[PDB]
Image (cartoon, rainbow, N blue to C red):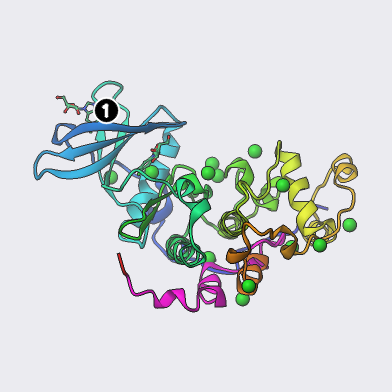
Amino acid sequence: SGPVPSRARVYTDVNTHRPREYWDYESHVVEWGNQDDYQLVRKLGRGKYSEVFEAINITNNEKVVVKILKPVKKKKIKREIKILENLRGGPNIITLADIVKDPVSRTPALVFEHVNNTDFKQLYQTLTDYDIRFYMYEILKALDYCHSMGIMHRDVKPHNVMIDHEHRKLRLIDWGLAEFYHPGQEYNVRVASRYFKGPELLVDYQMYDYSLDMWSLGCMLASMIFRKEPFFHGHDNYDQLVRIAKVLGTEDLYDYIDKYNIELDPRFNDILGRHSRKRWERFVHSENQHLVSPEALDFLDKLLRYDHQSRLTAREAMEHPYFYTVVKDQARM
Ligand SMILES: OC[C@H]1O[C@@H](n2cnc3cc(Cl)c(Cl)cc32)[C@H](O)[C@@H]1O
Ligand SMILES: OC[C@H]1O[C@@H](n2cnc3cc(Cl)c(Cl)cc32)[C@H](O)[C@@H]1O
Ligand SMILES: [Cl-]
Ligand SMILES: [Cl-]
Ligand SMILES: [Cl-]
Ligand SMILES: [Cl-]
Ligand SMILES: [Cl-]
Ligand SMILES: [Cl-]
Ligand SMILES: [Cl-]
Ligand SMILES: [Cl-]
Ligand SMILES: [Cl-]
Ligand SMILES: [Cl-]
Ligand SMILES: [Cl-]
Ligand SMILES: [Cl-]
Ligand SMILES: [Cl-]
Ligand SMILES: [Cl-]
């Protein structure tokens, strides 16, 4: 007997109701732009599959950000491009303005609207209670949008949120691991950075959905309000689940496992053993008390659930009391 089927509780069929060409990215064809219209100004950074630069469009002197892709599975290139095009005009999602070829390698170079070169991780351990709420809400706007457009981000982490703190503007970036959701489809669990991976990934449950992003989001919130980086500090994939189990307790883990009839190695269960739930209030210390409210803990508790189907949706999260006042922000710069 295999694992129990799952479908998203929200936006289940959004891709089903759209034309094939919306999501069948394997049959997309790229309309290239003129590389010569852009000139790189300076290097912002280099990562795994990319180098990112500041650049200018010399036709109108508009400053842009240019991400030059390093060689990857060509199917994945089409995937990211199609996703970014689909999402253009979404709230707090990076805007793909053009696509050009690298003069040297002829690899694709993605041209984006300009954004300031500061990521959330650089700021997020020193925000006020108010600003955590504010920026959490802005991230939710992005996630609800991309989920509503049938897209899982699958790499929600501090390093993937760019912030312009001066102008209170935030963009969700790094859509290279994003994927279209299709009910019934089994997905690769090698997504998301360790500290942000949901229990579904860690127990090899493949029929997951947008709710993975909500787990990652919860991991970000816990980090911010408790001033702990990362909140769940696993040393390997197995220990990531152990760390989660030492906070949420094993009782609910084995209930989740039993619910979806998941294939858990008894030798992993021996190491998991039994751990008591560690009430969310246990991670409060004098350092972080001014950040931890009953509404914060209620919210966190409702995001950080083993069972992906119990997790708040992005819309449900946006309606949570944690954001009750911050939605009234008066946009002071
Ligand atoms: O004069 C040669 C011009 O080629 C631009 N250039 C070099 N490598 C590039 C890679 C990319 Cl993705 C782009 Cl858009 C422009 C590049 C340089 O930025 C320079 O302005
Ligand atoms: O290696 C870390 C450095 O790389 C920059 N970076 C990585 N991916 C990026 C994507 C965008 Cl859109 C921007 Cl603006 C910067 C990026 C980060 O902003 C940081 O300056
Ligand atoms: Cl597909
Ligand atoms: Cl295109
Ligand atoms: Cl990160
Ligand atoms: Cl990006
Ligand atoms: Cl996949
Ligand atoms: Cl993948
Ligand atoms: Cl993995
Ligand atoms: Cl931990
Ligand atoms: Cl137990
Ligand atoms: Cl406790
Ligand atoms: Cl309080
Ligand atoms: Cl749970
Ligand atoms: Cl959602
Ligand atoms: Cl709720």
Taking 273 as reference, is 164 left or right?
left
Q: Residues within 10 Å of mark 1 (few under 14, many from 20)?
A: some
Residue located at (57% from left, 45% from top):
192
Q: Nearer the viewer, residue 151 or 38?
A: 38
Residue located at (21% from left, 32% from top):
41
Q: Nearer the viewer, residue 52 or 220?
A: 220
- In the image, residue 321 lies in the stretch drawn in magenta: yes
Residue 149, image quadrant: bottom left
Q: Quadrant of the C terminus?
A: bottom left
The CB of the residue at mark 1 lies under 8 Å from ligand 1: yes
Give the residues in magenta. Answer: 302-331
Please provide percent x and percent y for residue 255. Answer: 82, 61
The amino acid type found where label 1 is placed reads Asp
Using the image, determine if residue 298 lies above or below residue 25: below
Residue 297, image quadrant: bottom right
| Residue topped by disc 1 | 102
Q: Nearer the viewer, residue 25 or 306?
A: 306
Q: Is residue 240 visible?
A: yes
Please provide percent x and percent y for residue 65. Answer: 27, 41
Q: Nearer the viewer, residue 89 or 305?
A: 305
Ligand 8's quadrant: top right
